[PDB]
Amino acid sequence: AKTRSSRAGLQFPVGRVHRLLRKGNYAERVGAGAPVYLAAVLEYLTAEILELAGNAARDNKKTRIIPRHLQLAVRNDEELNKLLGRVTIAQGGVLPNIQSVLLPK
Amino acid sequence: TRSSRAGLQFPVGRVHRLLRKGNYAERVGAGAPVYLAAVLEYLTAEILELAGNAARDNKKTRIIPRHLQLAVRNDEELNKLLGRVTIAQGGVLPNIQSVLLPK
Amino acid sequence: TRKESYAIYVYKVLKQVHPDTGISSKAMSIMNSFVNDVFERIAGEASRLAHYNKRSTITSREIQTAVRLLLPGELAKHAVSEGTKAVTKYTSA
Amino acid sequence: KTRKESYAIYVYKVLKQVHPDTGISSKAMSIMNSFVNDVFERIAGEASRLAHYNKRSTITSREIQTAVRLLLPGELAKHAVSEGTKAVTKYTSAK
Amino acid sequence: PHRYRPGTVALREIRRYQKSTELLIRKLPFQRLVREIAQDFKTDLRFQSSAVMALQEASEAYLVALFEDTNLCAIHAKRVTIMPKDIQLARRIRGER
Amino acid sequence: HRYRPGTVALREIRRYQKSTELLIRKLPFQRLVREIAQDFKTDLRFQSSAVMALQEASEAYLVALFEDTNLCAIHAKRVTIMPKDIQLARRIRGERA
Amino acid sequence: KVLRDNIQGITKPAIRRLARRGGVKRISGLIYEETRGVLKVFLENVIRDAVTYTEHAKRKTVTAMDVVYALKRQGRTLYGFGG
Amino acid sequence: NIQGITKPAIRRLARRGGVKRISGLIYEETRGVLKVFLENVIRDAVTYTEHAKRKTVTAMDVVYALKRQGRTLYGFGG
DNA sequence: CTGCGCAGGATGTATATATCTGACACGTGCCTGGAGACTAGGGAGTAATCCCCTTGGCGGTTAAAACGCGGGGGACAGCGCGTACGTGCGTTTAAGCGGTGCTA
DNA sequence: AGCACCGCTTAAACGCACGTACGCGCTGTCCCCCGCGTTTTAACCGCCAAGGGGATTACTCCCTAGTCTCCAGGCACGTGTCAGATATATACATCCTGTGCAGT
């Protein structure tokens, strides 16, 4: 294979992640494993998220992942939710949670 | 130098080195080490100002960390700037909530 | 003009993971944001590590430890393994 | 015995410029040096993104300037731009 | 006739607005507001319609986050009704000014 | 004689806000630090400045925290801080969940 | 044409709707003005910054991107609009 | 060890904190709190040391950690 | 002759349908960013020496931690008053729609 | 593509009426903290001792920037259809209705 992506057996474009790291003034020089590693970690996470979004889409009987589905995904996962603990998703909405003391007895 | 040529006390050279080496951009203008060294100089003055004041107020010739803290937390604009900074040996401003006071 | 995007790679991975499932324009957009955010966050913190250690170059050792600061546990651990795997894979091939 | 740099001596000179008959402790000197480096990063950093954001390769006094306007509170910014624009023009005077 | 008891429609409305994602502030008012504030910073500014929409997305998120934490403060005080003083405690604690 | 309950409290507040000296004695703290780090890596050494740094950062943080805790106490018409306050403080800070 | 009092566009039923997605059941009457107060300090912050980017980009039009960069600056990162 | 963080020490911090009256359960709560704090900071710190290939955690690792966590500290080589 | 509980209505939500529309997802073709192959140069890694900083262990006074005692005032729970805020309806206002035109 | 400007449509907002149930002010009790005196631990300081590890130095070679030529991965562009939004009828749930039936 020609694509460095294939050499790494990755979906993400390792050539892109390589250009970016240079046109980005993070350091003089960039290693060759760093793009690879990063391009992969990017993939793990998009996968990790898309997984939970799809499930969210499924319960809501839907073919197509819309941001509510990403939002539900993110704030239901303790850990993803913390990675994006200071982030807003356009059209997210919030998690259904109503405080106890506001419920009738 | 260039500190001279700009009336600055702050090392205009040092600064130009640091910008180039600290990976902020490919190239680095001639004005910027000067503009910045100045802003750095400006702000260190405002602190040294109000701390010194505070050391006078607290009756000492030498500035200790506290005098910095007092200068900083009492200045509304400086305190914002250093809104997320803990200053070693700063202590706190004296502030006691009303309802806690005796009747 | 050319507006680059991770729209294809995100599709690819979605198809790998939920093959009967499509993404909306907005959703894509969001995804596309998330990749970029985590890119900088990682890349930046790696850059600090090079710097802190008087070092001129970001190697995957950096990108790794960057990851160990940025991500929470299970996420970090998996991501690390996932990452150092494709490097190993990449060297050999 | 390694030659570690700081801003110490310049902090002092400026101290004299404002409070001629006053001194400083080492402990507070560190704080002044920390303060300088922190502020230097924050401004430099902002400037850096500014360039990128605008598909441009150079950090000029202008970039620094607007960086300052994002980093600083209304009044402190105001004076800062002064001293900034001043020392620059005064610099471009001499040669 | 018929009359839902006090607090009954509140609970309903909460559930309504917690299921959806559509913006809660009306679109036009919102814009007028943003154009004002921006004018008073620099005259003669235009906006990408998506740039308003960004600020609103960002605005509502904040306020909903805010009410969340306000609400907690009401409840902290053995109360159920939110009050300016509640908001005020949330913002002091968030370290807003 | 006897000072009325709470009056040395006020007096102590005054004394500590006037001083900048550290309030946890170094060695227990130091031993706490080494313990916690051992759990992350074995056979480790600390610079004495590295321990001070931690100490300052931690105390300053806790004081700040009591400040905000204390406001919650007060928000609840109380005068005694209680764990339920800290939890609310931190919750709103977004430290705890 | 001149613009005046627009904060009162932020009607009471809306400041309500937000509070509901916020989990609030009972709303004190003195809340609606405090919210407008807050929303204003909020928009004044994002737009002061958005604008500073717009001025730097030497533009008369404020873009979705200037907004997004501002939010990121203020630690209120936003996905969905570029960046 | 943790209980080495004495009641009186915790009391002083709350005094400098502006606090007048302290419940008994606070003390222990404080401890969990302080623990969580150090952990996170020391986790990040050590990670810097592990990456610097050193058996000696420096002040700068600490300082870098506090920055990471948005609790910047001045006076140990900013 | 009276209080509590049961039944019953009407209200909103839930859902089923059919229905109409435009956005995603696809295929086609055109170009720019990555691949490929090569060089030359300096970073970093490694090994070889140094000394500084950290740990450690020891013993003296000395403050600080501990512990208990006793009673005061603050927490908390119960109650009741007074009223503000939720609800509903009729009245009123301007948002949202899509459609056209102009130049920044 | 941003602003402007217009009018057909109506969903939303406003304003007022009413009373319900919550904010808060009062009380009243019970105990959990504060004060303070004395009894118990280990913090601290000063002093020396030993070797780990970090700091500095000189050397070679692997790795990465830089450069060129070569071409399909990735983009915009176009297009056709089905997921999903919208409108409208209908069944299912409950919150509050007004009655009877239970007990004094």
Image (cartoon, coloured by chain):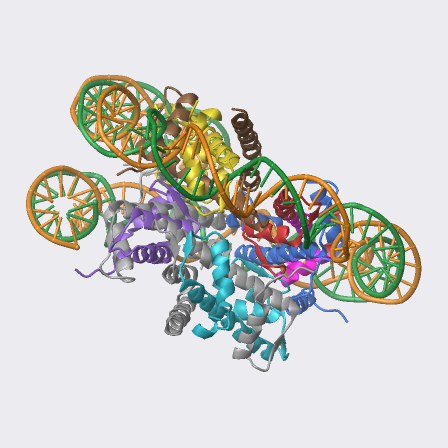
Chain colours: A yellow, B cyan, C brown, F blue, G purple, H red, I orange, J green
What residue sits 64% from the left and 79% below the top?
Answer: B60
Q: How many labels sit on residues?
A: 0
Query: Magenta span: helix, strand or loop, mainly?
Result: helix
Residue G23 seen in the current view: no
What residue sits 48% from the left and 25% below the top?
Answer: A7
Based on the picture, tell me whether residue H13 belongs to the magenta stretch: yes
Q: Is residue I34 left or right of residue F69?
A: left
In front here: G30 or C84? C84
Based on the picture, tell me whether residue A1 belongs to the magenta stretch: no
In front here: B66 or H20? B66
Q: Is residue B54 above or below residue C41?
A: below
In front here: B94 or C31? C31
Question: Residue A24: which quarter of the image?
Answer: top left
Indicate the position of residue H37 as horizontal and vertical percent values: 62, 48
Question: Residue A65: which quarter of the image?
Answer: top left
- Residue extent of the magenta highlight: H8-36
Question: Residue G5: which quarter of the image?
Answer: bottom left
